[PDB]
Length: 216
Picture (cartoon, rainbow, N blue to C red):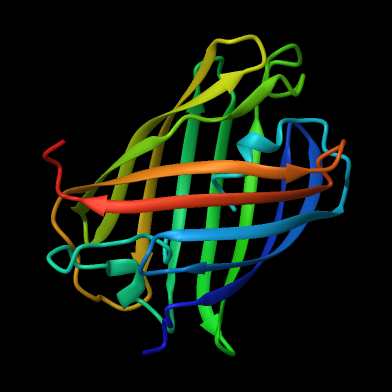
């Protein structure tokens, strides 16, 4: 009942990557039970960014994941109060992103507050040289641990070049109340940058996400 078949969200993000501070705001919309969403983002402080938008796009919404009836939808169950998540991305060239995030449901809309910290990206690497070209589809391995929901995956960035740039990704999702943890499952995710201005101070994204048992 609080999560309708159509839901909007608002997002604020603050952080820094290799010493460069920024803020981003966005508005989005999607169909939480179909696993689909779009958003319009803008850089509100510290634009233009000297690094690849691609490292921020996965930090920009797990209430929008289609779940079968027989896998508890822990993150939807957490609303209206919501959940927090924390993430580390270890990139193959020593770059690291850590994230902390709050999600809640206020005045009929999801509210996201994100804090992103990137460091140790090589100055001549594809991130700081803006030579990435979006994520391959990812398959997140979900499992309950220590009273929380954990996800682990290898994410693959495409390079302008024709090769790949990997990150090992670990996330912990913690509902604000102890709503039902699921068992082990997979979430297939694909995120697209669908529009942007020249300097990526204005950007649109689409994501589709679907949970399924870990059988193929």
